[PDB]
Length: 330
Ligand code: NA
Image (cartoon, rainbow, N blue to C red; front, side, top):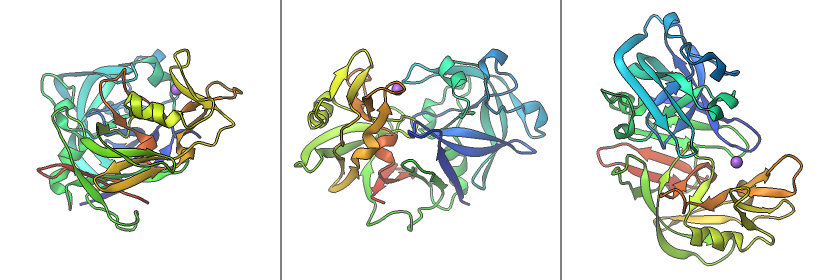
């Protein structure tokens, strides 16, 4: 089997992407944030504290003929941005882009933090990291990908995120029309439960490529590119007037600037992020200070190849016995 679903930016900045997901019988379609940096499929629901729901579409298990309470199971998750959610668990039928899994754990939120409530466009998360990170207790649950894998034509999914435009998540096949040149595959460590890999270096604009190992994770659920402070300083030093602002919480730059591109290495291959991808616009409405899309990881504990980086590539998440990542230009 295969599946193919379109993923759409939630706003004009590409702050996250939402993908429609069918849950239950008859189908309830919710727009979920596919997150290769976490491993829980959780939704706004009929159980979510009413004051914490503001415009989201909810899953109502009582209206699904295939929903089962997963008795005794609870979940609770905290993300790298400080947001959180928790609740109880149902199993139900879940379909993405025509690919169906029966018996998927659907984590129903009883509580969500303010950033979730305030974002009416995201009805929940669909985690695509390794199932070792799933938070359900006392019986850990599998991701949608892990449950689908044995049915798939090839044990893979691909992320093809758009810049200011829709893109695609495919499951079970690699669309050879969706990229240019060849795919370069690189090793993955699953030790921390992430799609963790090592980039071979970077370049800023037209500058020389610096060969250097940068461990990090491929994370579709993180908006920006978080890299070591040395790398980030080298990038923003090429933008007149850019500076790190502790009041704003990272690098800012004059909105009048033209940003240089940023290149990262994948083995002997190179992925180029156009400068435009690194502009996240005015810090507050009407400001002439703009927020940068490349930020320091130093206060995180891991480097994160988030959407800024991933959207410049066609990315293969190879879930074979030995997992690998692939990157192609597009
Ligand atoms: Na922000």
